[PDB]
Image (cartoon, coloured by chain):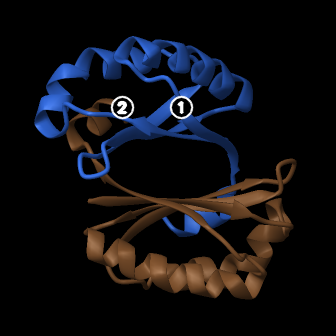
Chain colours: A blue, B brown
């Protein structure tokens, strides 16, 4: 599997306000091909947000990354910090 | 719930070789205070490795980060790129 980790400068909303505002966005991610799950990350303290995504394959993950990076611009995000990694299943299974 | 995202330059082992080698390490992590789960990440083509961790609280996450970043020096890992984030539960539940 492929893990996508992303974060970026963000000035809010955070917490329950973020959940309410970005609910539609979250639901749309579920319709993405190859998508398995996502953990939403946020740090009001450091003014940043992002997410950890698990995709079935790298191609699916890269396609989403490019698209989401474009979309993020509509929220005022000019730079996205992201890394694409392979997941080590054996080790991950032990720690889950 | 606090999420820890870490990665760093790495020269190996990778894949099953990594799974066999670090298996003992994965078992000890399960014993760490406040530990919930970890996803092992790796990229042989980019010569990098790391992990995504979930801890019950920030102090537990920060305690482990301090301990782990120090231990990694033994594997030759001089520097580590780390980020500590809060998790948005509502949105994360939608995407799982």
Residue B29, relative to residue B87: is it above or below? below
| Residue in the picture at 36% in, 39% down | A49
In the rendered image, the quadrant that contains the N terminus of chain B is bottom left
Residue A45 or residue A25, whichever sits in front: A45
> On what subunit does the disc labeled 1 rest?
A
Gap between marks 1 and 2 measured at Cα: 21 Å
Q: Which residue is mark 1?
A: A80
Q: Residue B62 — which label?
A: none
Across and down, in percent, residue B85 comes to 35, 54
Residue B54 or residue B23, whichever sits in front: B54
Local crowd size for mark 2, using a 10 Å CA cut-off: few (<14), some (14–19), many (≥20):
some
Nearest to the eye among marks 1 and 2: give it. Answer: 1
At numbered mark 1, what does the secondary structure look like: helix, strand or loop? loop
Across and down, in percent, residue B6 comes to 56, 61
| Residue in the picture at 62% in, 19% down | A66
Badges 1 and 2, same chain = no
> In the image, B28: left or right of B73?
left
At numbered mark 2, what does the secondary structure look like: helix, strand or loop? loop
Q: Quadrant of residue B78?
A: bottom right
Residue A84, relative to residue A87: is it above or below? above
Q: Which residue is mark 2?
A: B95
> On what subunit does the disc labeled 2 rest?
B
């Amino acid at each position: 599997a492929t893990l996508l980790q992303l974060h970026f400068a963000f000035n809010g909303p955070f917490g329950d306000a973020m959940a309410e505002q970005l609910k539609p966005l979250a639901e749309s991610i579920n319709q993405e091909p190859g998508f398995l799950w996502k953990v939403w990350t946020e740090s009001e303290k450091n003014h940043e947000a992002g997410g950890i995504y698990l995709f079935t394959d790298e191609k699916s993950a890269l396609a989403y990354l490019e698209k989401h990076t474009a979309r993020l611009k509509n929220l005022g995000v000019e730079e996205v910090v992201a890394k694409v990694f392979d997941v080590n299943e054996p080790l991950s299974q032990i720690n889950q």
